[PDB]
Image (cartoon, rainbow, N blue to C red; front, side, top):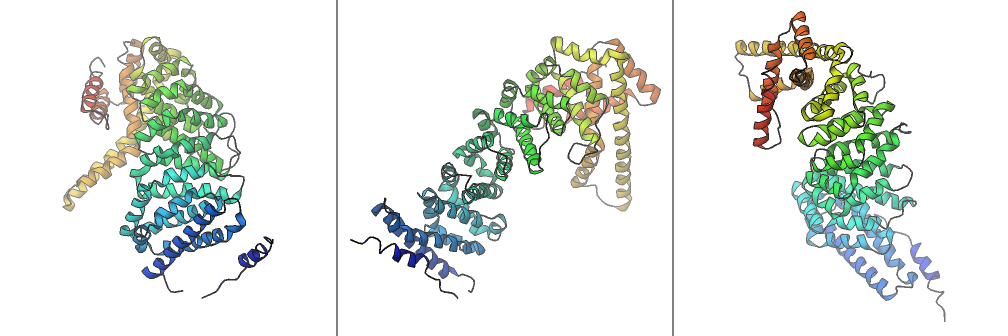
Length: 511
């Protein structure tokens, strides 16, 4: 017996040198390369069946299999030949190797897959890109990549890179095919991203990457937003954000992660079904606590509250917000806007924009005792809040009039010039009005009109009292509101826009 003269002979093999030598691969270089890949992949699979308990007997075939996969990164240089990888079933083979028993192999193909699906690489060949992406999606890449992901140890660097490269793949496909975000998320990816986020590990760069991918998956995709709801993802997001309620993020990469979660949270609140979830998950209480602490997360917390209470489906959140003493929190922000001395936060216009969007949401949705508590805020201290509302009114009416004057002047200049006023000219105009503070001013006017319909004489009197003693007309407000009611509910049923139009306009009588 001597089974010790084949390991000594094996070491002489894995230390064997390599011949040296070119010209950019043609279709025949790739053909030769793929055949070798199938040749080595078949030998390795066969040897692992023959000697499942004797690694020495199949490890030089696995070394060979790993070498060809590394070598195939060159194919990404010329995406015109991607049709060859599909026709010759290299893609079906590679996807099968994602479930190879050795983790070193599966990692290797994940590295190859991300190199092949590089965004700049894919745009080099529209024809070659489509055929590759179609093979990947039909062969269920995201499903297989996730399955392989579940067996990776992140305490091992080579496999931590594998997790990263796996995510890099989906960031690539979702940019080339935004249509596959739904399929990808439902193939277990979203489920996995949630687990990885709430995993009790320290903050590494892979957690930052997960927060980033999750935002992409939820971007204008109502189907994935509902999916995140079913998977109890709102709770995960709230739990992760609750770390930064009293403390700021240590590093800067952790601060960006915090914002990627805030993005995902707002993105989920776009779906009405997630409003009740955010409510049951005590998100309102959390957000309100962040406003009281006044840490870094104070800016995005205000944004979340606005998204939660906005519209008809935010009516339950509006009532709960008042219940949890939200009024004592929001009105100080209404009186004075926090200053931007830092670098990462909302501006003054952006702050006042959300506060006014919040009050307008409350005035639209609140009923019962909660509505009275809101109106009483406007009466207290000799209606100082009404004075504050008017100060804001004149500020944005001023900025708006300056912009409107500049816009109308250009219209006249264009007429003498002979230039026709385009539809892409009128759209350029609308943008100048927006960052002048149009949306803010519209909320300020809606608030003004709603509290004058409250049949509270001290309020209605003060509004008219301030309006003329400054010079502005009650008619200017009526103009802004008609314009506001017109462009309402963009993204909702024709029935909705019709009834809300009626409702808003009805506030102009009895004003």
